[PDB]
Image (cartoon, rainbow over all chains, first blue to last red; front, side, top):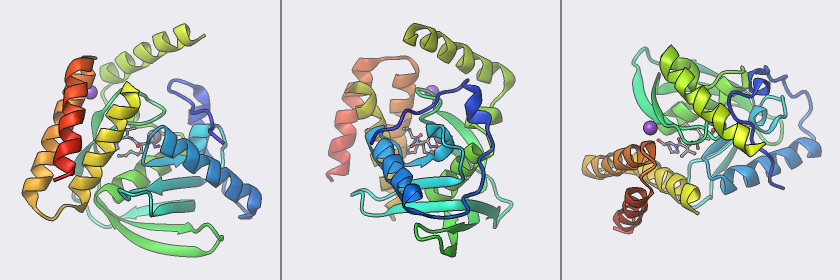
Length: 167
Length: 61
Ligand SMILES: CCCCC[C@H](CC(=O)NO)C(=O)N[C@H](C(=O)N1CCC[C@H]1CO)C(C)C
Ligand SMILES: [K+]
Ligand SMILES: [Zn+2]
């Protein structure tokens, strides 16, 4: 099913997600809905926080043919470089805005897979950006938090106006 | 629709950039993404529609 995506400045996006303790079929059903929502948006990743489910679950697909859907449960990342790279990021919870964010582009990922089993992965390039963006969401962080005060406020006021029309 | 087209084009170019070995393919991808960003920042739907169509072709190459 398609889930509703929360949008900045909704305060529920600031919730810190709780770890998943059991990877049951109810978790896999949520993952399946997260993928459907992501593919339809479209986006290349999604965190459960964004669909108002405050559990530590991230989905992703960086394949051109939708052949490599990836699941990250209770994800953590650790930089493997002090080098910083820029990437112009957008966010389905900050729709319509694309801004440069500085992040390490080499990290180690630790998480549980779709069966609940642990794994580790070294990530570079877009996968390194995406996992940091998605983990940020699980910690209640949005990419606009890296921007200047005035740029963030212009984005907030623009979205608040769009939302007033939505209601 | 328009928004989905813009997003899908950005995704396509970003993945081509990531998976490309030739830095000239990466440059071309980055250039089309910048035009999309600039057109979408101005809500210039006409240029966005034109750039999306060019992006689809350069990816068919
Ligand atoms: C790069 C880190 C982005 C993580 C995924 C986001 C979706 C999201 O909000 N995840 O939390 C996305 O797909 N964003 C898209 C996006 O910004 N992209 C997709 C390819 C790379 C980048 C554009 O430079 C837009 C177009 C919906
Ligand atoms: K922009
Ligand atoms: Zn996001």
